[PDB]
Image: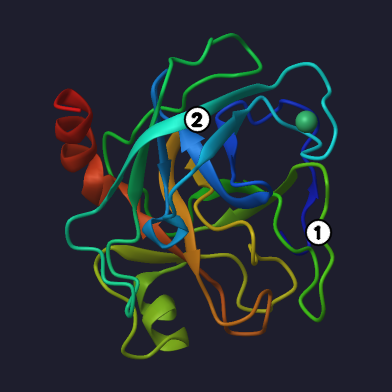
Amino acid sequence: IVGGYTCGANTVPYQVSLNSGYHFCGGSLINSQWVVSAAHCYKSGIQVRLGEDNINVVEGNEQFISASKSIVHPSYNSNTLNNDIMLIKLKSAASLNSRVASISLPTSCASAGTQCLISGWGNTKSSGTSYPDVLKCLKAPILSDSSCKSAYPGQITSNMFCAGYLEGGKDSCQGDSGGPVVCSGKLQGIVSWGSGCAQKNKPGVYTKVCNYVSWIKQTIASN
Ligand SMILES: [Ca+2]
């Protein structure tokens, strides 16, 4: 997260870190057994880390639980990033309390202009590299589909939205991928892609979660 703020420990209780020996992506806990992330985050050997603040220090609220299964969206295209969504099942159910908690799926799609909270342990610099150890947060509005398409000609599908600031300076970034965009207490987006980070006229692009609720629910019901 570039241009954000330190969230505060366990203030984003649905935020998870996906770990294979190191943090590599974010995700969102949507019930005691299941995490939503980006398909482009797929790999084998995932350990889900819940209750994290500093990902390099054991602070007392962590739950580390290995994934038993991953399910990449059936129509995920890694070239265009269309349908950049995946489900990860935990080998055992997480213990839910105020510091570790699921986030609700949307009942309807959020609109341009709605404020959301984007969070992650990704790079904090637009030029060069610095990774924070604690969770970073950014409040950002959803942008119009027109401005989104104008920013990225020929690249924005019906399964994507832009959020952030056309002026630059405030954005998600490398290492934030798969993490949440939450608006009015609902998971509305997944950190997906963008051209660098926090560049002028290159806002972040996010997976449009509301399009996937039926797939998520059905998949969970049978796995
Ligand atoms: Ca920790």
Residue, disc 1: 131
Q: Quadrant of residue 155?
A: bottom left
Q: Residue at x 66, y 75 (%)?
A: 197
Tell me the distance, in whole angstroms, between the alpha carbons under discs 2 and 1: 24 Å
Whether residue 101 is situated above or below residue 68 in the rendered picture: above
Side of 35 where 159 appears, left or right: left
Quarter of the image that includes the N terminus: bottom right
Indicate the amino acid at tag 1. Tyr
Furthest residue in direction bottom, as rendered: 153
Residue, disc 2: 66
Q: Position of residue 141 (x, y in %)?
A: 55, 57
**Mark 2: which secondary structure?**
strand
**Mark 1: which secondary structure?**
loop
Q: Residue at x 41, y 69 (%)?
A: 144
Whether residue 195 is situated above or below residue 161 in the rendered picture: below
Tag in front: 2 or 1: 2
Q: Position of residue 200 (x, y in %)?
A: 66, 84
* View quadrant of ligand 1: top right
Tell me, yes or no, whether the two marked residues, 2 and 1, touch with CB atoms within 8 Å: no
Q: Residue at x 25, y 64 (%)?
A: 76
Side of 35 where 86 appears, left or right: left
Indicate the amino acid at tag 2. Ser
Q: Check disc 1: other Cα within 10 Å, few if <14, some if 14-19, many if 20+.
A: few
Quarter of the image that includes the C terminus: top left
Whichever of callouts 2 and 1 sits on the residue coming sooner in the sequence is: 2
Q: Position of residue 34 (x, y in %)?
A: 38, 29
| Frontmost residue, 147 versus 85 | 85
Q: Position of residue 42 (x, y in %)?
A: 42, 55
